[PDB]
Image 1: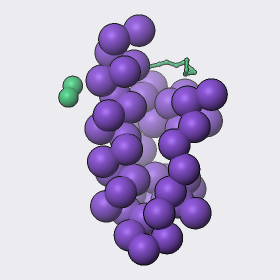
Image 2: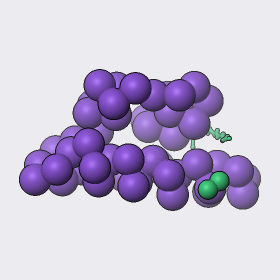
Image 3: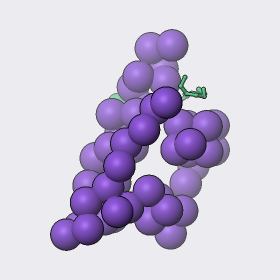
Amino acid sequence: FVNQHLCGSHLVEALYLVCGERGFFYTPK
Amino acid sequence: GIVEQCCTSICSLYQLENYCN
Ligand SMILES: *C(=O)CCCCCCCCCCCCC
Ligand SMILES: [Cl-]
Ligand SMILES: [Zn+2]
């Protein structure tokens, strides 16, 4: 799914901002 | 996981905070 690949890119940049010093985890599966 | 919850619907910043460490 390209549109899923595109969405994930935007999710990781939002997680980066939201989570700040805590960091985050990006698990597709 | 986050793709099922936040790519099928827009997640608020509060919902996105669920995937923080
Ligand atoms: C890994 O395959 C994800 C598991 C669930 C699949 C849901 C995919 C939905 C993505 C929709 C993107 C639409 C963005 C405009
Ligand atoms: Cl896009
Ligand atoms: Zn994009």
